[PDB]
Image (tube, rainbow, N blue to C red; front, side):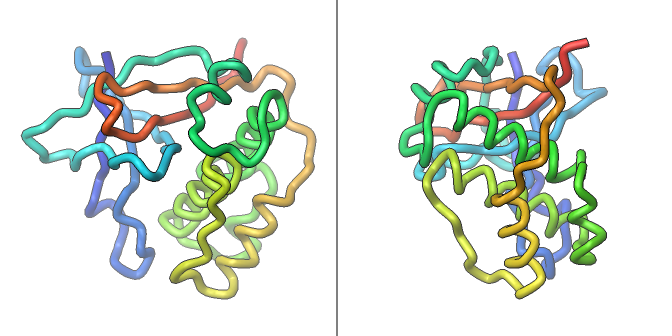
Length: 175
């Protein structure tokens, strides 16, 4: 069992990115992991200080399951899975293409853009709202990249006990 939460004060006001999301094992707050949401019409996980702890179950992110769970994906199957894997490989914090440094982004801005790039595929939603031109440039690079991804990178899905809340995803390497 995991809890998922937003860390509303993680980034400064100028990054316009409060909904930085993490998951944590309920049996251990020694470690937390960065994750990204999908199904944006649902509610974000509650803030870390909330008296409401939003619980999640992890599941292997197969193409079939991912597509089934996405409410309005832009593409389906392997293409949806691989498109998202690549965004994460190229986004915060993997940064495989050096996009962060190229556009002189802060950590918060880069993570925000990675989230927006995920939504482009999972939710058919490319939001440019409140972005600077360099952020728009970075986001467009991120969503249009076609670099090869490592062959052993896989998707983890996190499904909330309560369907009111957003689904979450992360990646890992099979070693």
